[PDB]
Amino acid sequence: ANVVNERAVQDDMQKATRSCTKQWLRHLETQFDNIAVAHTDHLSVVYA
Amino acid sequence: ANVVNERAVQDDMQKATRSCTKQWLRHLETQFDNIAVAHTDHLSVVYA
Amino acid sequence: KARASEADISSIHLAIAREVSPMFNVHELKKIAESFEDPSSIVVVLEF
């Protein structure tokens, strides 16, 4: 977040074009949290 | 980009109209990086 | 939507199998043609 936030203000682009990036970054949080249970419980025994 | 920036804040124009200028000034950068390999490697031996 | 491809099962299962397999021919990367122009090009960084 802090890398793309400092990069967008270097080119002083829109508030909406920067927040819609950061709403997408923590949408990847929500999609990661739903699949992180099934990787560490069921993919981890397959690699074992 | 610092000449067109102080020109814009002197006449207090929009955040979008100033950022869309600067997004174009680095769209020339990608188009200059992709073809400066072809000038300095094949145009320069033609001028030589 | 440029980076993300359709969910083909014959290459997702192939990616899991490469992790604990031996390597006999040295692998190389599918070429990613990016310029990192815009702050929206952080997608390729999150891909890595």
Image: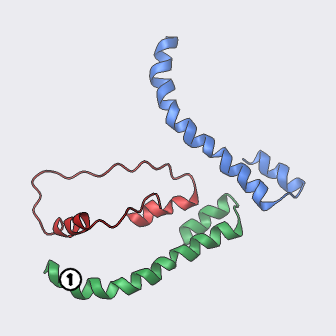
Chain colours: A green, B blue, C red
Q: A29 left or right of B20? A: left
Q: Helix or strand or loop: what does disc 1 sit on?
A: helix
Total tally of numbered discs in the picture: 1
Q: Is residue C23 above or below residue A35?
A: above
Coordinates of residue C36 in the picture (x, y in percent) = 51, 53
Coordinates of residue C22 in the picture (x, y in percent) = 9, 62
Q: Is residue A18 above or below residue A33?
A: above
Q: B6 left or right of A39? A: right
- Tag 1, which chain? A
In the image, A14 versus B47, the foreground residue is: A14
Q: Is residue A29 above or below residue B21?
A: below
Coordinates of residue A18 in the picture (x, y in percent) = 64, 68
- The residue most toward the right is B11
**Crowd around label 1: few <14 · some 14–19 · many ≥20 (10 Å):** few
Q: Quadrant of residue B41?
A: top left
Q: C28 left or right of A16? A: left
Residue at 85% x, 57% y is: B13
Q: Kindly identify which residue carries mark 1.
A: A44
Q: Quadrant of residue A20?
A: bottom right
| Amino acid marked by disc 1 | Ser
Coordinates of residue A24 in the picture (x, y in percent) = 54, 74
- The residue most toward the top is B48
Residue at 58% x, 70% y is: A21
Q: A3 left or right of C11? A: right
Q: Is residue A12 above or below residue B39?
A: below
Q: Quadrant of residue A44?
A: bottom left
